Length: 225
Image (cartoon, rainbow, N blue to C red; front, side):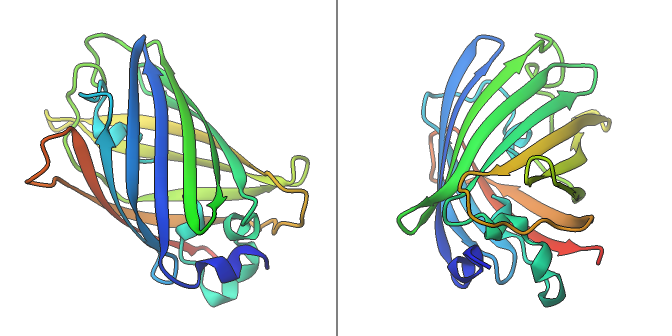
């Protein structure tokens, strides 16, 4: 396919987010690199408007699936890379159990040789005293499976999954994800058979960094075929 060749080495990544959660406005910038050969991502995010109003972990999924490692035998199912360099639109709705929801819209594509993820986030109906606004989530992250399916009507894919956020009291905060991706260009893309992505992520901090930020290491590989 098209994009395949674009991912053959380490690619620099730029992440830009504009958000509003219950009237609290904020901006985030992130930079790093991805190496789809190992399904590996390394990023650092910085809250540019000051203190992040929600917990960092809640934004992970929002902050580039084209960096997933697809095994040789599954290359024909890699929609993400097939949409490059023109890119794709990724939209979601994220429902926090017994809490508010996030609505996101992003464009992911290449600007020169940098892979760009530009997002607009809108959060509503959050409880001032819930796990999100109340900042009760631990600073860590779990492994998940992300289910993918073809959408022949929109020439895209539909994706669904649940994230499990650990709460400081030992409990769990569920986050139901509903997602749609559609190509930006008019060129051909690869529509996949049902399959899934297996994820793992580690969160850390930069000891010498005074701004509000998050350091992220993540591995993702496709499976189920």
